[PDB]
Length: 244
Ligand SMILES: [Cl-]
Ligand SMILES: [Cl-]
Ligand SMILES: [Zn+2]
Ligand SMILES: [Zn+2]
Ligand SMILES: [Zn+2]
Ligand SMILES: [Zn+2]
Image (cartoon, rainbow, N blue to C red):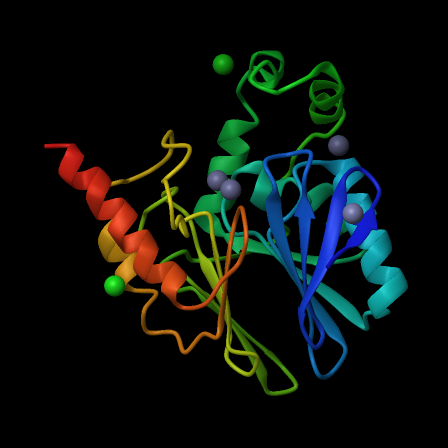
């Protein structure tokens, strides 16, 4: 089933050398952890804050003994950039699009106390206020994307268009046939609409059909197969229809 971690994280194995770690205190946010054939560990997205992320990195160190860690932010929300403080502290190489870095820096200008009020309880508010999110150390041009090659094993980061957020990117692992679609994968309901482009979302999701994926991992909730994309398109087009 799963391994129980501190701060209400759970880790589930979905393939050889591939795990999903879920932050169950903060909106059941999913984090992909994949060990490459050459020993590099790639982490996609993040827990919301420092206690969760330290917990994640302790588990990565203990169970995978990485040669090197590369962390890829999926978008500027805290499930995305909330891990950067601890990723950096633990020596990981953090990456995001230039737009994600810009949006995180702008978000940091907002009054923190007001932002923390939308959280469930006092314990979570205190944890959020005890972390101070930072952008990634390394950036790529959003529309160009980024391809890593770890001893000829590729990891492809690409922008399919605005959907859940203006900056959402997906991460594809061709050898493992694994697509981390993040928070633009919404097979039942679209969720938080604040930064969304609902009109663009159907065509942005249509761009995910090209991937030869056996597993599609969403930003929240259970992962599935390529049908996760089909479902998302229908959910988004339903919302667009309701809109006029
Ligand atoms: Cl404000
Ligand atoms: Cl269909
Ligand atoms: Zn359990
Ligand atoms: Zn988000
Ligand atoms: Zn700090
Ligand atoms: Zn999310």
